[PDB]
Amino acid sequence: GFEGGQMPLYRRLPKFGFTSRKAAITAEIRLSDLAKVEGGVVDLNTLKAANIIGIQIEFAKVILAGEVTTPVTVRGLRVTKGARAAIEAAGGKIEE
Amino acid sequence: PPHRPRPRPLPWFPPR
Amino acid sequence: GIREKIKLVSSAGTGHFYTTTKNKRTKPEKLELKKFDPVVRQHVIYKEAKI
Amino acid sequence: GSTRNGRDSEAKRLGVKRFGGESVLAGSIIVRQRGTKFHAGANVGCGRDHTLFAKADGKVKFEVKGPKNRKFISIEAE
Amino acid sequence: PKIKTVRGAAKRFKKTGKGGFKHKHANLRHILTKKATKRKRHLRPKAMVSKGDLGLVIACLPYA
RNA sequence: UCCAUAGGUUAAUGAGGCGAACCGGGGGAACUGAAACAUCUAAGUACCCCGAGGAAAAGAAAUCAACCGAGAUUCCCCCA
RNA sequence: UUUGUAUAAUGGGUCAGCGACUUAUAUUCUGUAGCAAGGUUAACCGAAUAGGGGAGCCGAAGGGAAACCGAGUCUUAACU
RNA sequence: GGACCGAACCGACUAAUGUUGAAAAAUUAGCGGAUGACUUGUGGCUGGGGGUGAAAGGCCAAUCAAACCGGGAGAUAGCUGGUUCUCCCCGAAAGCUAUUUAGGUAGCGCCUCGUGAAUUCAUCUCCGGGGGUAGAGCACUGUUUCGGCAAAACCCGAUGCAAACUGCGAAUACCGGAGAAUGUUAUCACGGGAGACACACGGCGGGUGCUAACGUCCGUCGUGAAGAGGGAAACAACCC
RNA sequence: CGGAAGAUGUAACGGGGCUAAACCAUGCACCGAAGCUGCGGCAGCGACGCGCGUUGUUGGGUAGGGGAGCGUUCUGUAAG
RNA sequence: CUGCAACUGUUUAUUAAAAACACAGCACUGUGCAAACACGAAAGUGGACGUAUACGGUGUGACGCCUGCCCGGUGCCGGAA
RNA sequence: GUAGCGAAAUUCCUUGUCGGGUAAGUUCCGACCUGCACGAAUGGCGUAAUGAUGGCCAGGCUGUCUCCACCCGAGACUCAGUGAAAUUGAACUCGCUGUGAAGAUGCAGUGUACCCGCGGCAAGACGGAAAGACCCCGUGAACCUUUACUAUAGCUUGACACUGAACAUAUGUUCUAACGUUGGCCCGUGAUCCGGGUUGCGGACAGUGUCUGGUGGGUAGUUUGACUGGGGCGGUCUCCUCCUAAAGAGUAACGGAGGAGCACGAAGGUUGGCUAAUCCUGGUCGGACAUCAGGAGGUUAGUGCAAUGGCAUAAGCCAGCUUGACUGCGAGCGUGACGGCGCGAGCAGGUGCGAAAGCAGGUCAUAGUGAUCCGGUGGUUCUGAAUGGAAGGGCCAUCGC
Ligand SMILES: [K+]
Ligand SMILES: [K+]
Ligand SMILES: [K+]
Ligand SMILES: [K+]
Ligand SMILES: [K+]
Ligand SMILES: [K+]
Ligand SMILES: [K+]
Ligand SMILES: [K+]
Ligand SMILES: [K+]
Ligand SMILES: [K+]
Ligand SMILES: [K+]
Ligand SMILES: [K+]
Ligand SMILES: [K+]
Ligand SMILES: [K+]
Ligand SMILES: [K+]
Ligand SMILES: [K+]
Ligand SMILES: [K+]
Ligand SMILES: [K+]
Ligand SMILES: [K+]
Ligand SMILES: [K+]
Ligand SMILES: [K+]
Ligand SMILES: [K+]
Ligand SMILES: [K+]
Ligand SMILES: [K+]
Ligand SMILES: [K+]
Ligand SMILES: [K+]
Ligand SMILES: [K+]
Ligand SMILES: [K+]
Ligand SMILES: [K+]
Ligand SMILES: [K+]
Ligand SMILES: [K+]
Ligand SMILES: [K+]
Ligand SMILES: [K+]
Ligand SMILES: [K+]
Ligand SMILES: [K+]
Ligand SMILES: [K+]
Ligand SMILES: [K+]
Ligand SMILES: [Mg+2]
Ligand SMILES: [Mg+2]
Ligand SMILES: [Mg+2]
Ligand SMILES: [Mg+2]
Ligand SMILES: [Mg+2]
Ligand SMILES: [Mg+2]
Ligand SMILES: [Mg+2]
Ligand SMILES: [Mg+2]
Ligand SMILES: [Mg+2]
Ligand SMILES: [Mg+2]
Ligand SMILES: [Mg+2]
Ligand SMILES: [Mg+2]
Ligand SMILES: [Mg+2]
Ligand SMILES: [Mg+2]
Ligand SMILES: [Mg+2]
Ligand SMILES: [Mg+2]
Ligand SMILES: [Mg+2]
Ligand SMILES: [Mg+2]
Ligand SMILES: [Mg+2]
Ligand SMILES: [Mg+2]
Ligand SMILES: [Mg+2]
Ligand SMILES: [Mg+2]
Ligand SMILES: [Mg+2]
Ligand SMILES: [Mg+2]
Ligand SMILES: [Mg+2]
Ligand SMILES: [Mg+2]
Ligand SMILES: [Mg+2]
Ligand SMILES: [Mg+2]
Ligand SMILES: [Mg+2]
Ligand SMILES: [Mg+2]
Ligand SMILES: [Mg+2]
Ligand SMILES: [Mg+2]
Ligand SMILES: [Mg+2]
Ligand SMILES: [Mg+2]
Ligand SMILES: [Mg+2]
Ligand SMILES: [Mg+2]
Ligand SMILES: [Mg+2]
Ligand SMILES: [Mg+2]
Ligand SMILES: [Mg+2]
Ligand SMILES: [Mg+2]
Ligand SMILES: [Mg+2]
Ligand SMILES: [Mg+2]
Ligand SMILES: [Mg+2]
Ligand SMILES: [Mg+2]
Ligand SMILES: [Mg+2]
Ligand SMILES: [Mg+2]
Ligand SMILES: [Mg+2]
Ligand SMILES: [Mg+2]
Ligand SMILES: [Mg+2]
Ligand SMILES: [Mg+2]
Ligand SMILES: [Mg+2]
Ligand SMILES: [Mg+2]
Ligand SMILES: [Mg+2]
Ligand SMILES: [Mg+2]
Ligand SMILES: [Mg+2]
Ligand SMILES: [Mg+2]
Ligand SMILES: [Mg+2]
Ligand SMILES: [Mg+2]
Ligand SMILES: [Mg+2]
Ligand SMILES: [Mg+2]
Ligand SMILES: [Mg+2]
Ligand SMILES: [Mg+2]
Ligand SMILES: [Mg+2]
Ligand SMILES: [Mg+2]
Ligand SMILES: [Mg+2]
Ligand SMILES: [Mg+2]
Ligand SMILES: [Mg+2]
Ligand SMILES: [Mg+2]
Ligand SMILES: [Mg+2]
Ligand SMILES: [Mg+2]
């Protein structure tokens, strides 16, 4: 960081933002991961058992990433608009 | 003016 | 360095303000200008207040 | 003794940025100047500091018009 | 031992998708009345660290 | 000083000293780094002192957790 | 060592022996090998350089200070 | 009698010698005190920011503006020195900017290695450009000399001068476009590794200095640096 | 041509010497470098044909970057 | 003949012996005794088995003639509404 | 600034001037006063005696000298025995003039020189010795100073604690029972310690702990800039304009010249209008210059403040109406190593002026400034450590030293 005595870049620029505690316990699930659970019911606990999300994750979002071929029942998770389309197209259903 | 001090002695050290 | 900083506060009660300077000796009367208040999105009267 | 001089200001990089026949995009600064040594002709704007800039794409053209023999810069839409 | 993050740098820079860094502009903390609105408006959004500076930033943030 | 107590004498039992490291506790620097330096660092380190053991110390929730639960202490790998 | 040294600048009397870019961990890049949308296990268990152990870590998604949204997102009342 | 002269004894004023000494403070000849605030033996006490000092920062084991020994300890050293076998390819810089910075360091420029994208870049020819330098000039801003007219200035003339004068104005240079030929891809981007940020002289354009300096400070080219060979008696920087 | 004096020794053509062996002009010969050419050899980079051939071009270097090797001690190969 | 220091003393072991230090004498000041003051986290000890004609600190430096003006500044002493 | 003293251990000018001493006296002695810059216990002036003390003069004396000679011893020298040292890149190790990292045994040119000892001398080998002590530098060290900065021992103040009781009106007096006693006597005890006892005297004071203001070079840790034709002293340090600057940009010096550290709710916006200086001629007070009229002139004026570039379609001057000195953005471009700084058509919202086309995101342009951290104020569809809140944090606006 030392620049010969000139105020270094990381000191002449301002600090910004704060760190969310909620972000640390939130995860994202790819469509490609929905097939890796056991039973075809994607909930928070089945995702953990399948090593998809960490043990201390409380919230998870399914996003449109990869593909989903099989029918899966997503229960309790948030799902993006695009992911909702993909899951329902594959024969799955989203329970709130 | 003088550009050198007048010569002086050194302290004794164990020689070898 | 005689001109003091002032704030012009919105009369719309939005809490939105502009800042400017003012020579308080020469012009003691309060500054009052219609300016755009972005909170209500209208030109409203803005009136002088302490910075 | 000493000196009472020893001061100057930073150089301001004025002057012509795009010469005759150069193709410029709209927005391009053509000349930076103090006061209007050059005046804005067709498709050229004059900024608050008398910067001349292209208001359209095209080629820069210098020209002398009028009785005073004033220098105009214009953009030939190309 | 593990390299230590320069903690001050981590509060000022955030890594973007293609691996650059964003930062907040200097000169918008105070003395705002004298500055033109245009100047201030252009300092509001976050900017990207420049090529010359990336090396310095990267060194400070080994786990970014 | 009236009882008494302090004091005195005898007996029995025990202690003291040494030891490379490790361990607990009482005290506790500075050079150095910060491109100077005082907050800060070095470091509760070096060193001094007391105590102890084959290990020591710690230890059986007025602990965590998060509305689900776990279940003393110590040590190792993660978390980072 | 210097702009520059036969320099009258430095160093060496000579010989023999010794005498200076290392090691650990983290991190990034290059080469190379394995496997590949996956890759790899740590401590530990195991007589096992085997085998177990996937706790974890990195990667396959980003945007935003954040809630949050998500192939988008932020900005803005809204974007050509 | 802190009296006098003077040996022992205690000192140490002068000179010579000695200075790898006979000696890490002496010898020789002279010199001061010599009943006293004298001198000396033996033992004891005071300990390091501490002692002790009729005070010189003196003395505290040949050591003193903070003893010695061991430890923290391989303190720190932007400084000096030194850094060990071979061959091949390329090959700098001594600049800018910032710096409690100036002999340090950082980003950029310049080197190297790698990856990627353009007939990219260079030379010349033609075409399109802006210019205010050289030169010149004197309407302007100033300065200057002499005349003709006048209440001895202007007006009317002649004559010079200018980095900070311009009613003028090149050569070159620079920017852009087009075209051929040639060229070690020489241009640009990104990434790995640097070094360097004391420059020197010569030519040309200048500031400074005395149009002094092997002087100093810029611009630009060349050489030295990091380049041997031939020439200039000898001679980094000149000529080839 | 005079103007024109300096300190160790000629000492202000490098020396001898020179009336050209000086100067000016013109010319033609020759000498002269690690330049260029010739002959032989090595290496880099690139074409071109199939690792080899043919051909162009390049090969002074400090800091420094890149590439490729030699040799030393020790372990396996080696109860060889 | 003259400077300096009254004097005898002391001093830079090892380049300075002096006009430097000390000194008797002088003055100011503190100190009432469990003294002030000093060494010491303290206990204590020195001062002193002393007691203001005593003790500590400070300056001056035999003796002779003397020691002028300034209390604004800084210190010290005293006052307190 | 007295007495006293004064060219002085003090006098720069200065060898002051005068007198004495010498043939000749920057020293000496006596004076003078023009004391650069004496002066009364950091004492003034005198002073017998004393001094290995400083200065000056004379007699005596002399090899100190004119100017050395001779002699006696110890070395030196030769022989026998023993046998060091510093230094040392390698040496086949001459003069001169030139050259050259600028003072040559080693280069050039040239002169001279058979090989090798021994006694001597010191001109050179920038001879040997000690990583210059001067000088500068290092964001080195030490110790010393102080009205440098920051602490702190000590000293001192008050509050609370140990610490209680009466009485009178927070303050005083009295009391004894805490506490003190370095008073006396008794015991432990053969004891100037210590403890206990008795008694006296002090007495809720003193003293100690915690907290607290003051004082605090007594002690400690540190700081005390850079540039610079060496350093110091002086000047300078950021920004703007011109010249140096070589007709694109940029370009240095302790080069040559000047400015800034603001101003303005109009001096900003817009619409409509307008055009200067200076001189000449005439005219009450009125004059060289006030205001009026006409002419010439043509911007020689004006522009809020330097200079430069601009300005008549005016950017100059006057009036009407105003708040665009707007909010969200921004194709593109300029200029910086970077942090940054600048120009900008156009788009959305809402506005002003104008009949309208239009113009307006401050001012003819270029100076008028300061990062980050910490903190303040207002707002906020963010966050809120079990949960609901809140604190705190974020974001937007803005402020401070
Ligand atoms: K420290
Ligand atoms: K440092
Ligand atoms: K320091
Ligand atoms: K040197
Ligand atoms: K030397
Ligand atoms: K590595
Ligand atoms: K790899
Ligand atoms: K977008
Ligand atoms: K003794
Ligand atoms: K010490
Ligand atoms: K010793
Ligand atoms: K650099
Ligand atoms: K590179
Ligand atoms: K003229
Ligand atoms: K040059
Ligand atoms: K070259
Ligand atoms: K005398
Ligand atoms: K006297
Ligand atoms: K003496
Ligand atoms: K003394
Ligand atoms: K006074
Ligand atoms: K006083
Ligand atoms: K006098
Ligand atoms: K004087
Ligand atoms: K005194
Ligand atoms: K006296
Ligand atoms: K004496
Ligand atoms: K020769
Ligand atoms: K000769
Ligand atoms: K000699
Ligand atoms: K009592
Ligand atoms: K009390
Ligand atoms: K103090
Ligand atoms: K200079
Ligand atoms: K000089
Ligand atoms: K206006
Ligand atoms: K107006
Ligand atoms: Mg897992
Ligand atoms: Mg300028
Ligand atoms: Mg803010
Ligand atoms: Mg430091
Ligand atoms: Mg045991
Ligand atoms: Mg135990
Ligand atoms: Mg040199
Ligand atoms: Mg040479
Ligand atoms: Mg030599
Ligand atoms: Mg040498
Ligand atoms: Mg050296
Ligand atoms: Mg040597
Ligand atoms: Mg994400
Ligand atoms: Mg006597
Ligand atoms: Mg003695
Ligand atoms: Mg003797
Ligand atoms: Mg005697
Ligand atoms: Mg002294
Ligand atoms: Mg000694
Ligand atoms: Mg010390
Ligand atoms: Mg250490
Ligand atoms: Mg060391
Ligand atoms: Mg090459
Ligand atoms: Mg600074
Ligand atoms: Mg000219
Ligand atoms: Mg430098
Ligand atoms: Mg330099
Ligand atoms: Mg240069
Ligand atoms: Mg020149
Ligand atoms: Mg030079
Ligand atoms: Mg010259
Ligand atoms: Mg060099
Ligand atoms: Mg050469
Ligand atoms: Mg040559
Ligand atoms: Mg030659
Ligand atoms: Mg001669
Ligand atoms: Mg040849
Ligand atoms: Mg050749
Ligand atoms: Mg060949
Ligand atoms: Mg070659
Ligand atoms: Mg080579
Ligand atoms: Mg005298
Ligand atoms: Mg005496
Ligand atoms: Mg005596
Ligand atoms: Mg001595
Ligand atoms: Mg002596
Ligand atoms: Mg005295
Ligand atoms: Mg005299
Ligand atoms: Mg006289
Ligand atoms: Mg005489
Ligand atoms: Mg006299
Ligand atoms: Mg005096
Ligand atoms: Mg007095
Ligand atoms: Mg006095
Ligand atoms: Mg006296
Ligand atoms: Mg012999
Ligand atoms: Mg010579
Ligand atoms: Mg000889
Ligand atoms: Mg001799
Ligand atoms: Mg020498
Ligand atoms: Mg040295
Ligand atoms: Mg101190
Ligand atoms: Mg320190
Ligand atoms: Mg300096
Ligand atoms: Mg230019
Ligand atoms: Mg040019
Ligand atoms: Mg340059
Ligand atoms: Mg205006
Ligand atoms: Mg809560
Ligand atoms: Mg809570």
Image (spheres, coloured by chain):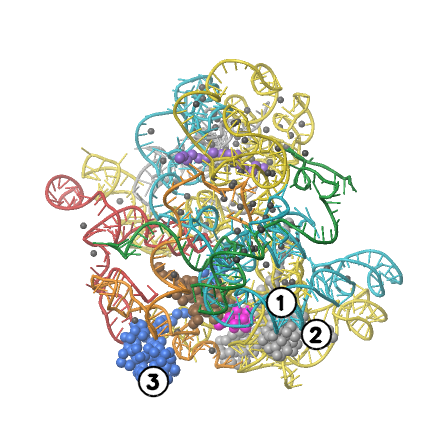
Chain colours: A blue, B purple, E brown, F red, G orange, H cyan, I green, K yellow
Q: Residues within 10 Å of mark 1 (few under 14, many from 20)?
A: few
In the displayed structure, would residue K264 be above or below residue I70?
below
Residue D39 at what x, y percent from top left? 67, 74
Q: Is mark 3 within 8 Å of ligand 50?
A: no
Q: Amino acid at mark 2?
A: Val
The number of numbered badges drawn on the structure is 3
Label 2 with label 1: CB-CB less than 8 Å: no
* Separation of marks 1 and 3 at Cα, in angstroms: 65 Å
Query: In this rendering, which labeled residue sits more in front, label 2 or label 1?
Result: 2
Chain ID for label 1?
D
Who is closer to the viewer here, G55 or K342?
G55
Give the image location of residue B12, x and y in percent: 42, 34
Q: Secondary structure at mark 1?
A: loop
Residue shown at 35% from the left, 71% from the top: A24
Task: Quickly name the residue at label 2.
Answer: D64
Disc 3 marks a residue whose amino acid type is Ala
Q: Is mark 2 within 8 Å of ligand 102?
A: no
> Taking G50 as reference, is K200 above or below it?
above
Same subunit, labels 1 and 3: the answer reads no
N-term mark: 2 or 1: 1
Quickly name the residue at label 1. D14
Taking H166 as reference, is H73 left or right? Answer: left
What's the CA distance linking mark 2 and mark 3? 73 Å
Q: Is residue E38 magenta?
A: yes
Q: Which mark is residue A90?
A: 3
Mark 2 and mark 1 on one chain = yes
Q: Position of residue H89 (x, y in %)?
A: 49, 58
Q: CA distance from mark 2 to mark 1?
A: 21 Å
Please report contact status of discs 2 and 3: CB closer than 8 Å, yes or no. Answer: no
Q: Secondary structure at mark 2?
A: strand
Q: Which residues are magenta?
A: E31-45
Q: Residues within 10 Å of mark 3 (few under 14, many from 20)?
A: some
